[PDB]
Length: 316
Length: 316
Image (cartoon, rainbow over all chains, first blue to last red; front, side, top):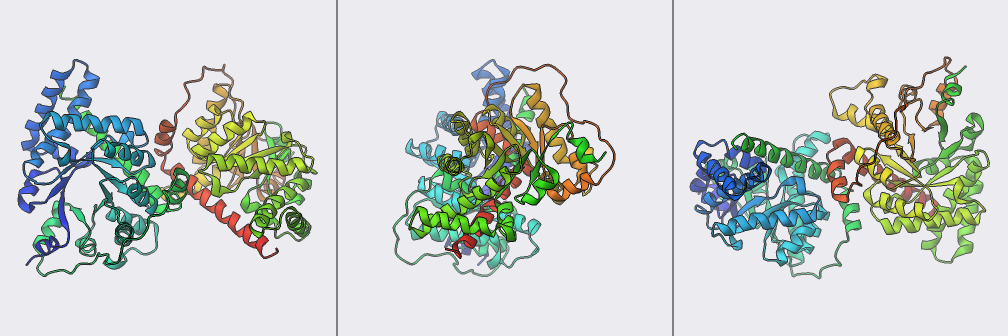
């Protein structure tokens, strides 16, 4: 059989894209989106109906142009989520405005607002994951949201400190970025080529997976952002993996069964005391890669958000 | 006359070193030290008396080896400060353990402890500046310390967000790191050479100086960490400048008067509302250079601290 079919025996496959064409092709359980993917999806011709629909709905909700752009942008993200949920049995991840990454209160409010839009469309919370950046503020926001029945996807996770804080907050799922970790080492270290087993991103996710299962944490571990199928195969066994369509295609066109790589067969160990903010900050900042990548990822998503509001603005 | 003598007309000269030999040579008003400089100074033969003295004093204060290393390390820093105060009419800056940079409570406690040691030696607070890293936690610590009569030197300042928060907290002085800003651009940008007037570090300090005088803030602006005399000359007029002995020597051996570069001749403007933590975090992290350099500076100072404790340990 093909690699994709073989991977499904050990890992839940998730599609990382806002394009429904991929859902039909690979039949993933869940789908993940992001500001960047929403922006690209907005270019898709058949998605024009979703945009006009969002704009029309916005104008019917208020007469203030400022508020219309926000309602339009949020409604578009939800409309795309709605089309995807018609093709996948699992969940859709929709990301909150990245400009709110360091504001717990604003992030909680935005998350509830997005949930409100999905609920108004008749979709229950069990089909959704609110995606937020794994800053200390985002983690604190998610801890609160989970208690209120809103499941979260903690993304842009790079340091072990972030992984630990997320597990301790009891979030539903985390999204460590394998590929971007590789990018940092390629650009800041002497070594420019890595064997799958030595790929820094792979090593990072493997360690997080071990720490999570070893302590009985229920948080789902979903590796994301890949650079090659090598990283994916080396993580076979991870709870879930969200993969871009291009890599999904490569796996499906590859023959040969693969073997499970990630597993924890021991007994559960006792959990330590919770990490405090001060300890979190010290440990996260001890990681040069994580320091750079977390801040950068937030900057980029914020820009994608602004570009999307721009596009929507010229339609009001 | 020489450049050094000429600079003194516009700017207060401060020596950046723990070596008293420099104090006698350049007669600076103040002197600044740091973990790294304390470590190097510990190598100076004539400083052996200061080390043994610190160790002896520590053993007389407690019988616990753990506490002795801490008392010894702190007492050494203070002993060096004491030798320097005999040669300078101004203040000495002594830095708190960098491992406490993200802990407000612990930083306040450490600062008071160092102040206690200076007071026990008969030195009043007006001759001292407690040096802390300009993280949000360090700024909050300094705001509190200033209210209690303890003046602070907010160092490792890189972003405008840090500069603004420091002024709003009413700290006595800030130490923006000119040279390290240049290092970042040389290593992460295409351009590897800069004219003094276009040096990123120089531009950064000039903008901070303008913002401070423009709004009537009393916080002293002291540029630090230089790479060449060009950066120094381009900042003539800055309240103070702390310079390494090697650059102090270059200025003294250079002939030719210099002209004032930094000045604010307008009227004071109204101050805006205070920046909040969320806004601070967003703005600081918008600066790739500041993100990298702040975290890095803290990591290095922490290591210097550990090395110093090592050295002291092998003497107990």
